[PDB]
Image (cartoon, rainbow, N blue to C red):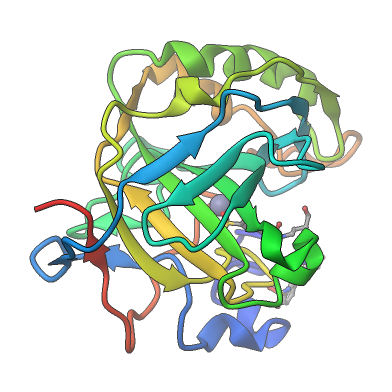
Length: 257
Ligand SMILES: NS(=O)(=O)c1cccc(NC(=O)NCCCCO)c1
Ligand SMILES: NS(=O)(=O)c1cccc(NC(=O)NCCCCO)c1
Ligand SMILES: [Zn+2]
């Protein structure tokens, strides 16, 4: 199957997912001197008060926390978005070294990791329908920088021992994703895609200006996860990021000056 190694990684994906070479692929480099401030962009509305987390799981390419999206509990609205998008899951991408790991870059700078909070457009009824639409998903991307610890991440970090290998999952109820946000909601936005197969061109990307700070010990625990399943040769889950893709006929807009 696909992965992030030399024999199944991003340079190979197009052979099974030809949209990998499409017109609105993600991630991209955000050139801060080419992004345009758009004073028409509304502030984001992050309404996570009623979020209901369910499980945390190792799916062989990241770890993911899932949420009950059977009704408008945790939603993302405003910003560039029309209508209401429900939080479905979040997951991360990270590096083997602190100078790499993020998918988006800022002026070619790579961050140690990147958080993706994945939301789907309720007008399409279910997520499978949404992924077929150019405005079906909104992913809120947040950079992780190595510095002080992020207290709202520690509960995630402390359970990763229990989902070391692909296919493992654990209960992860009563987790508050608001603890993963930075102070500012200033953002860049552009139309793009999923950054993993199937690479569907269905995502409004909203990337926050302000990174969150996580400690070295927190990101070390990401790097102890495994791509493999139990009983298989161990392969550390590191460098699960796609590099920046051609911007092509797109403009990145900024909500701030
Ligand atoms: N899904 S994909 O990235 O297009 C892809 C393309 C080519 C091979 C793979 N999987 C592979 O196993 N490639 C190398 C073979 C190692 C066999 O044990 C996935
Ligand atoms: N990395 S991302 O653009 O935020 C994103 C968001 C939502 C879905 C995906 N891609 C996938 O879930 N691919 C399915 C992989 C099958 C095993 O879990 C990527
Ligand atoms: Zn992602």
